[PDB]
Image (tube, rainbow, N blue to C red):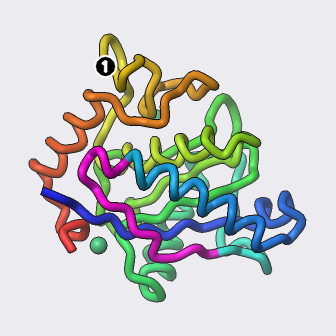
Amino acid sequence: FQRYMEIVIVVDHSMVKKYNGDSDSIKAWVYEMINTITESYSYLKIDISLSGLEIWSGKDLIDVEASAGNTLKSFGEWRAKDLIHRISHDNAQLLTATDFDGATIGLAYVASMCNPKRSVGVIQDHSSVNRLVAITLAHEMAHNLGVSHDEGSCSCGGKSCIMSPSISDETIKYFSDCSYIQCRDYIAKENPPCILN
Ligand SMILES: [Ca+2]
Ligand SMILES: [Zn+2]
């Protein structure tokens, strides 16, 4: 049974600076990522719809911190207080050029699909290869859908897939059988209504 996920991508001010204010360049970068993950999600029978793309060109609407956990929390709260009343969507992801403390390049709440303040994730625009960033984006969204990291013999043809605990050159842009299983059982068990439409 097909599920539909209406998402909004939010681009922060550090990203706008990183791209020298070129809003079109920013749109092309984000669009290519969406193109990539739309395919990956189709194989889990989840249709991705880009409901909106918000760019914080004037200034950030939250304080994006080096602390990934602080930023994630602030982002969800801002989403619930502001964003959901302007655009109807099921999930929102923040794209930032900020380098978070430690090895962290993305963070997200687990099993929180449809929660006003928790159906969110944060991702660092960590690579010049669009594919690597798209994978991180897919990864955090997957955490919202209750999927955990791959391990052992989980595979997607090869063994290094989207839910790999490490992002690299050899990561395959597809979800493993493990991710498929976990994702579908979460939907089956929790059946979040917002992705039913
Ligand atoms: Ca929806
Ligand atoms: Zn993860």
The residue at the point 53 percent across, 27 percent down is: 171
Q: What is the x, y in percent for residue 56? A: 71, 74
The vertical placement of 139 against 50, above or below, is above
Q: For this view, does 141 lie left or right of residue 102?
A: left
In the picture as drawn, the residue positioned furthest to the top comes out as 152
Q: How many numbered dots are placed on residues in this image?
A: 1
Q: Quadrant of residue 196?
A: bottom left
- Residue 31 magenta: no
Q: Quadrant of ligand 1?
A: bottom left
The residue at the point 68 percent across, 58 percent down is: 29
Q: What is the x, y in percent for residue 185? A: 14, 42
> In the picture, which quadrant includes the C terminus?
bottom left
Q: Nearer the viewer, residue 191 or 172?
A: 172
The residue at the point 12 percent across, 56 percent down is: 1
In the picture as drawn, the residue positioned furthest to the right comes out as 20
Q: Is mark 1 within 8 Å of ligand 2?
A: no
- Disc 1 on helix, strand or loop? loop
Q: Nearer the viewer, residue 188 or 71?
A: 188
Q: Nearer the viewer, residue 149 or 64?
A: 149
Q: Residues within 10 Å of mark 1 (few under 14, many from 20)?
A: some
Q: What is the x, y in percent for residue 175? A: 37, 35
Instruction: Indicate the amino acid at tag 1.
Output: Cys
The vertical placement of 158 against 54, above or below, is above
Q: Which residues are magenta?
A: 41-54
Q: Quadrant of residue 191?
A: bottom left
* Residue placed under numbered mark 1 in the picture: 154
The vertical placement of 155 against 103, above or below, is above
Q: What is the x, y in percent for residue 3? A: 22, 61
The secondary structure that dominates the magenta segment is strand
The residue at the point 31 percent across, 12 percent down is: 153
- Residue 50 magenta: yes
